[PDB]
Image 1 (cartoon, rainbow over the protein chains, first blue to last red):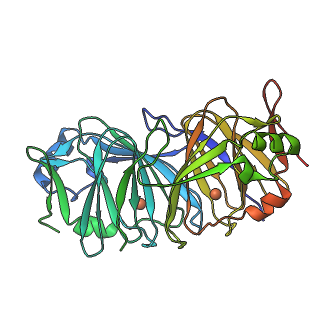
Image 2 (image 1 turned 120 degrees about the vertical axis):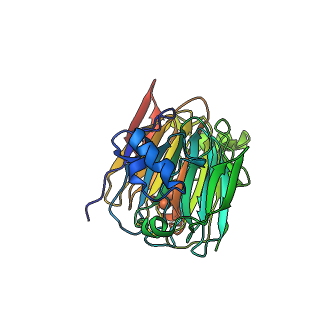
Image 3 (image 1 turned 180 degrees about the vertical axis):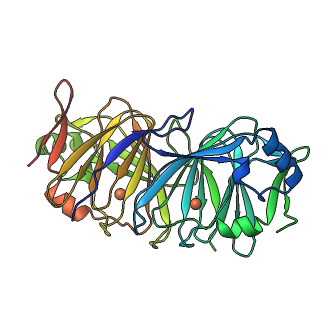
Length: 187
Length: 183
Ligand SMILES: [Fe+3]
Ligand SMILES: [Fe+3]
């Protein structure tokens, strides 16, 4: 068979940008119905519709045993009292895992099982997080500076954004004299 | 369901909190370097450590992931730079991704057909090891070369082939980094 060529690409620790990577941008308007305070959401969109996070990805064909990787730049902010966060998802092939490596800023990862059992892992520069098979995951920026991290996952894992779009996570992460992880009313 | 977790990686030492540590000395690498005599000597001179690994692995299951940092110390066996043993995956189908954290070096890759490639690595470099390619890491500096590796949990290891055939190229120093044919 015809083999693929190996390669090296630079990752800027300060910006999170990966050379030759495919860039994706998610604005607040791309997250309709993800936040609890839908009025605060509407107001922020009309006021400017800021970018929530950008993604720089290098992915291969969806074949067993291969790997993809991507950095995410999650900007600081809140929709009411709820911290800026990624959309979150399960994998299409739900038993695929993922590994995250925090590079800059501060935040944490919210994970949950299909039953809604939740976990919240704090992340700071240098933190490596293991997302086990079957767990949905969402990253949260709980600071005032960009939260940058690298994600590595199986090329055939895919994304199930749908379940989350519909029901969301069982917990929401908000600010109240500190970082609070509480039950999600709509969940 | 397995438990998610976070562990701290030290950007300076490469040490990963709660990981399994392993060490490989020259004595653990018999028949890997070309200058057989320089090997015997350095081993009698107290075979020093070539590299250390801080690993966190899962059971050999499809779709899961293992990760580990390697601390590849500087030095040479003759004029041949300090390196890892190198290997193909049991399931040759599996790929791997490396992320350079400190020092300087490179990755030498090989296909079963005879094709070889050497990719330079420095802080920030991410290397994509495609399916079917055997790979070995080389330290071409005077300081420690530290990097993080991520690979499929079911990739496995096959040193046999390499341990016997070796790589088609060797990386040596001639007032500079030089990649040349091996025997
Ligand atoms: Fe994922
Ligand atoms: Fe490997």
